[PDB]
Image (tube, rainbow, N blue to C red):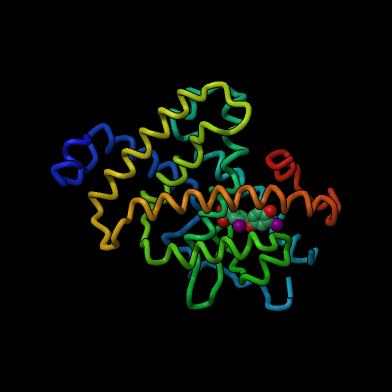
Length: 248
Ligand SMILES: O=C(O)Cc1cc(I)c(Oc2ccc(O)c(I)c2)c(I)c1
């Protein structure tokens, strides 16, 4: 593998890697709430709502349960994820949930209206998402989305990104650190090959793309912190049970 790099050939996916790519892709596609048809489908959250504004908060938490479960359904469709013990599966899910959800919203960013679209249906602006409880985390996700425009990602690259986030062998508490590292590596390798095959005409695409992983981990972490700030303001009543399970 390093030899071909040396000779300057950019390896495309092996047949086994194509199988894994099809699986992850299909997993994302089956749980990503598009469309190909999001955006003739989105209703714009009224300009006055979210002008912590609890009214805005209520709209987000109304659809958050489905958004979260869609992330769990994704992981469920990856066999490697199934080989892991219940404790790990849960620790992995709680670790990547917001990284994956914020990626999913970021890739639905629209320059025209300057809106992200949540859960495939609700288009919000930067201010509305900030004020509905995300604060600077909203800025982070909008800046990310603006930035991902020119990466021209496809369903496959978004799915691989998700699986790479999911298989983070460094979440606290994990039993199978080694096995989870191996899965991720296998995802990163398929991913990179897939990118060589895709021949994006951006220089240093792969490293640039990996920096996005780091940003999403930051978004996750900063969200954990926003979550505390919310528990103190908004009344625990307003938080859906699954929302609480995942982040507390
Ligand atoms: O679009 C999807 O499937 C995923 C998705 C769903 C939602 I609701 C969302 O907004 C959030 C997220 C966390 C949070 O604490 C609050 I308040 C609002 C984002 I960003 C992404």
